[PDB]
Image (spheres, helix red, strand yellow):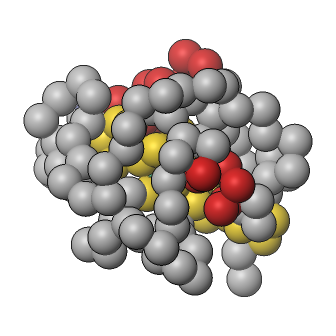
Amino acid sequence: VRQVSKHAFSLKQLDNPARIPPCGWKCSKCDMRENLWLNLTDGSILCGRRYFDGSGGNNHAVEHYRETGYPLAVKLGTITPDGADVYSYDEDDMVLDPSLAEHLSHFGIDMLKMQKT
Ligand SMILES: CC(C)(C)c1ccc(C(=O)CCC(=O)O)cc1
Ligand SMILES: [Zn+2]
């Protein structure tokens, strides 16, 4: 079972007015379009960890975490009405964020409108 993150209810979010679309996301820092992660603290959209074979992303999300401490991220394309995949860098697990709908609407996201990939 995934467990409620220790950051789910205490997470402090910054005000980021950028519009997040319901599909077609890109890393802010590179061309990656797969394995993108929205950090719930700042609204950053950045690519996942590079795979051992050099495929996958360019480590931009994890580097961002190492620089900031901002622990929770949601994998874009996994957001549905029923939830999403949320990773904790801090707890090094997939976690539950029962405030996810609130966290997401904070950046103007409607969970009902996001495309599954
Ligand atoms: C806990 C398991 C399933 C093993 C996992 C899943 C995702 C990540 C991530 O680091 C995602 C964010 C990123 O790639 O920057 C790390 C471990
Ligand atoms: Zn990137």
The residue under the point 49% across, 28% down is: 17
| Left or right of 17 in this view: 97 | right
**Can you give x and y, in whole percent of width and height, for residue 41 in the image?**
63, 33
Q: Residue 106, image x and y in percent?
A: 63, 43
Pick the residue in front: 50 or 79: 79
Tell me if 68 is positioned left or right of 34 in this view: right
Q: Which residue is depicted at the point 17% across and 29% down?
A: 30
Residue 89 is at least partly visible in this image: no
The residue at 37%/44% (across/down) is 20
Q: Against 82, is 54 above or below?
A: above
Q: Do we see residue 29 in this rendering?
A: yes
How many numbered discs sit on the rendered protein? 0
User: Going 44% across and 25% down the picture, which residue do you hit?
Assistant: 63
Report the quarter where the N terminus lies.
bottom right
Residue 8: x, y in percent?
80, 53
6 lies above or below 1: above
Residue 93 against residue 51 in the figure, above or below: below
Which of the two residues, 22 or 29, is positioned nearer the viewer here?
22
Answer with the quarter of the image where residue 10 lies: top right
Residue 111 to residue 25: above or below: below
For this rendering, which residue is in front, 23 or 94? 23
Res 34 → quadrant: bottom left
Q: Quadrant of the C terminus?
A: bottom left
Query: x and y percent of residue 13 in the render?
Result: 70, 32
